[PDB]
Amino acid sequence: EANLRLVISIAKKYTNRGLQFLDLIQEGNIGLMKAVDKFEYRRGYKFSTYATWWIRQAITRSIADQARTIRIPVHMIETINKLNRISRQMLQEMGREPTPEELAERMLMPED
DNA sequence: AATCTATCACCGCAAGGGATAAATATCTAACACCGTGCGTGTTGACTATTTTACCTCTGGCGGTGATAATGGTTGCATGTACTAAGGAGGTTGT
């Protein structure tokens, strides 16, 4: 209850058309349960930082592989999104259309 | 359903055109030979077909970070034309 607002200010970032303007807040409100259970204030650190790690990634996963058509081990989910993040160079440095042939040097790896 | 005279014409019956098939002569193809070289055979040494064993790849997925970060986003459902229903509440009536 004391943290229900911090769940909005983190979650609402990700609700940006992502799947809906709403639902990620309520999944953050369940990530907050694991956070409240493992709240090691006995290290010294603050619940702001706790939320910035754990509750943020509960908010991320709430529509990463949850609510999709498809779901995989998570390294192989967000790696598809590493490529979309890298494409921000491609679309302006090769800079007319995207080319997997450029992505091969930007990943140092074979396409297949 | 038979009779024919009297139509417009097919027959009455001369001509002649193309045709095809005979004989000739040309073509090609079918073959039989030869020669080439390849996929005829076993053997043998190679090296890496497969297996298992061993030593030690790739990628299975589980786990969760802390100088601190603690009031949020979200834009347009719709402007029209109808009108049936429920909702309101004061009151002049039932």
Image (spheres, coloured by chain):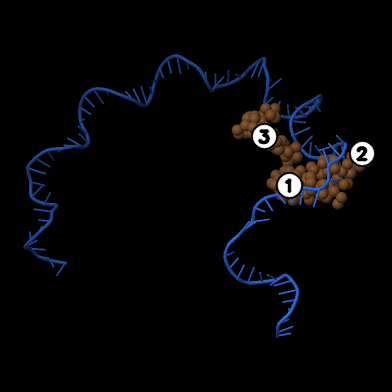
Chain colours: A brown, B blue
Q: Quick one: B63 or A61, which is closer to the camera? A: A61
Q: Which residue in the protein does label 2 denote?
A: A43
Query: What percent of the width, then of the height, locates residue B49?
Result: 67, 26
Q: Secondary structure at mark 3?
A: helix
The residue drawn where x is 82% and y is 49% is A5
Query: What percent of the width, then of the height, locates residue A27?
Result: 78, 49
Horizontal relation, residue B12 to residue B84: left or right = left
- Respond whether the residues carrying marks 3 and 2 are from the same subunit: yes
The residue drawn where x is 70% and y is 27% is A108
Q: Which residue in the protein does label 1 denote?
A: A15
User: How many residues crowd around disc 2 within 10 Å: few (fewer than 14), some, or many (20 or more)?
Assistant: few
Quadrant location of residue A88? top right
Task: Point out the image quarter for the C terminus of chain A.
Answer: top right
Q: Which residue in the protein does label 3 denote?
A: A87
Amino acid type, label 3: Ser
User: How many residues crowd around disc 1 within 10 Å: few (fewer than 14), some, or many (20 or more)?
Assistant: some
Of callouts 3 and 1, which one flags the residue occurring earlier in the amino acid sequence?
1
| Mark 3 to mark 2 CA distance (whole Å) | 40 Å
